Amino acid sequence: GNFKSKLKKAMLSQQITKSTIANKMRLKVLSAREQSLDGIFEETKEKLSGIANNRDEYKPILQSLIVEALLKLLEPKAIVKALERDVDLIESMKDDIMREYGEKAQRAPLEEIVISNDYLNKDLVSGGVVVSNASDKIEINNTLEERLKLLSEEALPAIRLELYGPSKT
Amino acid sequence: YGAIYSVSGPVVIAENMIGCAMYELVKVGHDNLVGEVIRIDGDKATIQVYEETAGLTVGDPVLRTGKPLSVELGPGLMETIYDGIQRPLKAIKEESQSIYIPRGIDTPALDRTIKWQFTPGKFQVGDHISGGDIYGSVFENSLISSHKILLPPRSRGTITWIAPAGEYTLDEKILEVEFDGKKSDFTLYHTWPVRVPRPVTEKLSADYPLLTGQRVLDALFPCVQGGTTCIPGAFGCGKTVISQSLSKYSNSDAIIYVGCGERGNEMAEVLMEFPELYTEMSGTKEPIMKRTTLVANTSNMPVAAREASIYTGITLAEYFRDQGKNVSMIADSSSRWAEALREISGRLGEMPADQGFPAYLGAKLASFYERAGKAVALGSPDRTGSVSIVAAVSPAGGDFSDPVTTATLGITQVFWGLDKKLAQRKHFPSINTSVSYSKYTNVLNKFYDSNYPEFPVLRDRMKEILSNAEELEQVVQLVGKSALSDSDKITLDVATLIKEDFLQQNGYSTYDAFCPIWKTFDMMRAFISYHDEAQKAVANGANWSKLADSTGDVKHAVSSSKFFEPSRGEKEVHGEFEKLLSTMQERFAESTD
Amino acid sequence: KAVEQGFNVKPRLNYNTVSGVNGPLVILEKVKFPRYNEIVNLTLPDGTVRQGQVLEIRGDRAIVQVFEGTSGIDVKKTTVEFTGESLRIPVSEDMLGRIFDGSGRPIDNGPKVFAEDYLDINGSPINPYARIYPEEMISTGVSAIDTMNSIARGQKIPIFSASGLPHNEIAAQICRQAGLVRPTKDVHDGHEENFSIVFAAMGVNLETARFFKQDFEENGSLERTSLFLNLANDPTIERIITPRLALTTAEYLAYQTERHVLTILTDMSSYADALREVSAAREEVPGRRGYPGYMYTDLSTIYERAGRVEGRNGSITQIPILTMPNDDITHPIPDLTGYITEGQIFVDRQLHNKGIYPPINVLPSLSRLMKSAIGEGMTRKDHGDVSNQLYAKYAIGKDAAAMKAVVGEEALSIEDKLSLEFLEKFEKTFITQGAYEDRTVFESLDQAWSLLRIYPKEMLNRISPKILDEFYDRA
Amino acid sequence: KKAVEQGFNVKPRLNYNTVSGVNGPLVILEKVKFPRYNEIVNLTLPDGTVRQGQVLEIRGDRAIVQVFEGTSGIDVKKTTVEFTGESLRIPVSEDMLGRIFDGSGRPIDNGPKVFAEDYLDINGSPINPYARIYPEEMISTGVSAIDTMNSIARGQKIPIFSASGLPHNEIAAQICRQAGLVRPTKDVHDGHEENFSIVFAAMGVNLETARFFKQDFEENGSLERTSLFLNLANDPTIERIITPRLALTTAEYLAYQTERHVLTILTDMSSYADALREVSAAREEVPGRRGYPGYMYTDLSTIYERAGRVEGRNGSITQIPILTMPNDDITHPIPDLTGYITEGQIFVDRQLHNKGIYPPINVLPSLSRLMKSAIGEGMTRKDHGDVSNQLYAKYAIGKDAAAMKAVVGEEALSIEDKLSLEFLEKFEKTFITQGAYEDRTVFESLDQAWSLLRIYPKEMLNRISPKILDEFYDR
Amino acid sequence: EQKNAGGVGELEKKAEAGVQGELAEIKKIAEKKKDDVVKILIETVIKPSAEVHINA
């Protein structure tokens, strides 16, 4: 028994250390894969910020995002918040967005879209706009950073089936 | 901004209250009765008013405060009696000389006029600080010396100015930290919402026993510093003895006694009692009131006060846990708190689930209990605190069918359930050694193996004897003792000896008032070895009637072993028990032949 | 010291806007700034005045419970003048000696009480720090009470009793025999050995009212008692405020005049019934048995106005008789009284059927502060252990009787047979007591010892051996 | 091909600042655009705290969002609630084995979010009754009292009924550490050909036990096969309803979309029922029997019946839903309904636990209805069924003869009963009694059972078939 | 006990060595497929599904 207690302690502690080390290694592999995925997402975010800069091709993207937000909100008068750089673009595309919402949805053309003076944080939002109902109560977020945030959660399985392929299912 | 729109008792439905948050304090009426919202309906906000609502009229202003029900933590609350809302009762009596607590009495929860000595601690100017970081130390009592004042858990930033050593009242600016550009201004006290647990870095495993004194509690169903229990709340003994025992001897560096729903005369007893409990406490005989807040809350006081009484108590206990003090929080009669929840729901109108209790009773008890962990405080320097609930549960008419006890049983690791038969026999303490349990028997083995190696084996033997003999008694009371074998007679008789001399404990005499762990272990050894000697002797020829007659002296010795005055110290009490056990063994060896 | 602040006239808004009336509560509309608890002097079309009380204001509506019932009220002609203040009983030291109707009107031939102060009936919370623990025992004389359930001066201790049991006789006996075990002095003056009872008969049949009146007359207590009678034929919501009226007069008497008062509240089960009626006509969420959810608080406010106070020589003992229905303690009235009141005297039916008086059953009876009004320096030294021993052996005897019923007498050990003999002699000679016996606690303890001496000294195990060796063999 | 490419579309989420009302754990919105019924929301507090909530009811343009993590702090003006477009759905992948998950699906350990293979819906779908197939082979649990003579078959859903304070919550850890197929024990071929896993699900466990589970699965090797879904007692109760659904969805994934078997554990389903009461009363539903909602049986079945083998897919979910006896009575709705849906019961008995036995399995009432499927020549040894039968019979004989030892004396018992007392002592102390960390292979446990039954002569083993005795009794 | 401690240290080192291969494979796969995953994510984010909610 004098040897039995300490030797059982030795075997139990060796098994515990082996199990803990194995768990740490498995979590390390999983966390390394997650860090690689986060690096891919960070490259995607930088690419989105870069794509927002080319205004010539970004204007259709902004108009379509505003149209999608207005269609989802489905209200006849909406307030749109955008960065200071895109205020002129929104003002120029107001009529086109009104007409498109009058055609994308079978509603009448939008009564009035007002660009808010509370500009979005240019240091965080890389692009897009955050539409809001006439009372600024029911607001939809359509910023490119927030869209990528939604996508990074709604398309993890597609990312896996793209990068790795079917494993054992 | 606001205005009353309905009154129905504690429920006062204000209006124009748009913007108020749920559970937010909101002064009510021109008397500024203190109330909190519990339902928001557009403008309106149903407020429970914590007061005698009589006299309120529509149009009475209800001015928000924007802070949840907050307890004023900090030095000064160590020695003081508090009401459920943390009203200092003695301060109320002093400022308002009448014997009545005036409606809507402001009195700060902590004495502002007192000037506490203060030492600067560790952090210096320009040094970053975080929530829970100790930045000072105040000499509160001779028994809570170095009450380490600590930064509020949420706030953080870099220090820009820290006051030097000296004396400061409660409001004095002690520390001025800067976060972003807005530099918060910190004083010697800080509030905290009682409804949210005080955050900790990490909750460890409670593994050092809370020596509660009563023999059956420490031996059969041990409790642990940082655990949780249910003393039965019976009159005379059980609750009454355990409260004083854990107050005086349990080595809990701080204590909070929150008597929610306790009868007024019982509190008047407690208030005249705790100032007089230095009789046998360690150190240099200081009153334990220097070491215990108590949250007095008589039943007559309004419902919401009873509901928030144990929240205030447990937030104070969490505060004293965040300084590394092994605080214990004796929540007396939590069934009264559950009744308060029942009737506040009834006023509120929501559909009750069980016996009229609200459905969320289980979740509410879980939230109140799970703040009982032994945890490291949140900020540097690292320090290990531990709060341990002791929630008396008045059993009412029923035994365990009452939904409060049933919902509690799924949470508390330790449950010293009452035994009606032992109470009717006036067998104190009267806990039921068949339905009680302690999920802390196995975690404590780390402690037992170092100090008392045979303690778990002896406890298992004691339980086995008691259970086998209760089985046997359930038959002999129906048939008779004639047919019992000698081994059966020994099991039954040793069970009677145990139940009368080990489990039973006066709790009032100078001996056995607080049975320390070593004396309890030695008596466990004596009784178990007596049973083993009897069983081994009758395994040989000797019939048991003659053996009992011949070793009545040994039986009386092991029975009167309880009389050993624990103040003699382990050095000689253990010697007495060694002598007793040796004479026991030699007498049984003699009488075997 | 002057109360000259009262010389002001506040004209009272007089409505005619009774929206509707159902059950005992009228409902009012178009009120201008209603107060939550202000009473209302609503006048019926007959010209009579019924004193209501606002129950819950809401905007310009005010549900008003109406004392004296709602029969005869209407909508077209009922006028409800609002007094601006809550119910305030005119209180004085001259009320001592005359009989008040339930709602404070003096049914005695004398005039209205010439009050020197108006106390709110709801009182106010007594600062628990300012409260002082009641330790002076009162010798109620009932041996079943003084020995094993000792009432201490300031304690609350309801006499739980079945319907039809003689709880009234027990309460009258306790009034007749009340007195501290170690009084201040022998003389009536200086010692003040007379409790100035304040008795509140609420929902009692008129025979009980006559019994209490003539029993106070015979004893001479009627010169120092304020009988708040609210009989059976008296209204059913007036029972809400009769206990509050009695307790606020008791508070005036004990705390503000340093007098010693024993406040009986008879038939508080009827109070719970009245509360149920009001809170079931309010469409409230009901509690365990249809009773209001808030019964605990509005019974604590009745009970917890008892006990001594620091700096005042007065004290409010109170013994609220409680007609527990169907004779089960877990009924929500006795179950919610056992919570609030420290201890209870359980008047038990099957003991009464066997002819024992008083039919007090010890095991369910309790006094949660008996432990401090005993021992040395107050009553006999051995009181605390004798009480425990009597309780334990009574329980053992009852268990032995149950076994004897279930299983033949053979299975009973010698201890069980001795316990059966002890229980018989107990119920027949110690619990049993004449209606005027007045057993002082010392001769009660002597009887208890002459009873316990049935057992061998080795068998009185709950008695400390010192008390045994000192008292057992004295004989 | 994989059709999961549909997940690349981005769906912007509306963010309503219109929380008109707040009531208990509910918040009530207005002017909502098509509010889906069951729909997770990220409710933002005024200070910026995100607090998940689940839509509980819709009416026109009003959605009664039920909020996790309490409700305190939710105002009417500044709080903004954002609708995620779909109901709650766990992200699943074949490599969550080894992640201790929180109640709401978020990994609570230091690891990262699961690289989801799929986002399976929580409630899943009922298993096609025609697509079930009968449980066939043993799923060894390492516990001697359970493996031999309360055996569990792949697909059976057998509970562990347990008293309030019994160590059932440690038997769960023991099973989860020691569970496994008998194929590796068979040693005739590769037993790891078809992998095994476990998906533990603790519901309502206090932190002193959740940390015990996490530590005891990390320290031992059981984590690389377990998906420990811990939610605490003070974690939001809606998460307590979610957790069993979470664990069963993970189990359905691992057992059908992949192929590995799984022995899912549901700890303390009584606490899950307690949380279901809160959900039911939140919807203002009237309480059914005992306070539990009348549809208790439906939402218990929709958990239990998500288990069993499947035609085609090789995997199989084995449930062992542990539940605490509310007051140690089978008649309680939760044990009654669980035994009414499950395939048996495995008691843990207070009486044995007070003797210090571990595990305190009470064999006499415990039974596995479809045990006979998992017992035979192919799986376990061929003598397993008769060993179980004989052990149960001799244990019953031992129990009643231990009852008679006190009635007819030890010497008057027949030699069968004397041998039965000896067998019962050795049984309860060596066979049922198992070290907390002692893994006993079913073959080894049967060897102990034989070493225990050879107390009796071959003639007294009437229950065992002679063809088995003639080759197993002597060895 | 000493052998168990040494084996624990050697097992930690061997586990790090074993996980190094898997981490290297993960980095290689990420470096190979990043240029395509980023392109797909950018196309999905920048291309909106302008469509009135069903129940228009």
Image: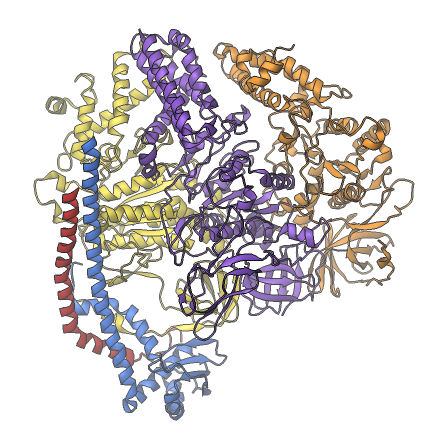
Chain colours: A blue, B purple, C orange, D yellow, E red
Q: Horizontal and vertical percent for residue D467?
A: 12, 24
Asked whether residue A89 appears in the rendered view, the answer is yes
Q: For this view, does B248 lie left or right of residue B93?
A: left
Frontmost residue, B412 versus C24: B412
Q: Is residue C434 above or below residue B379?
A: above
Q: Is residue C364 above or below residue B47?
A: above
Q: Is residue C205 above or below residue C8?
A: above
Frontmost residue, B513 versus C247: B513
Q: Please state the total of marks drawn on the protein image.
A: 0
Asked whether residue D305 appears in the rendered view, the answer is no
Frontmost residue, B163 versus B545: B163
Q: For this view, does B271 lie left or right of residue C16?
A: left
Q: Is residue D425 above or below residue A27?
A: above
Quarter residue D381 falls in:
top left
Quarter residue C234 falls in:
top right
Q: Horizontal and vertical percent for residue B327?
A: 47, 46
Q: Horizontal and vertical percent for residue B24?
A: 55, 62
| Quarter of the picture holding the N terminus of chain D | bottom left
Identify the residue shown where x is 82% and y is 55%.
C41
| Quarter of the picture holding the C terminus of chain D | top left
Q: For this view, does B207 lie left or right of residue C42?
A: left
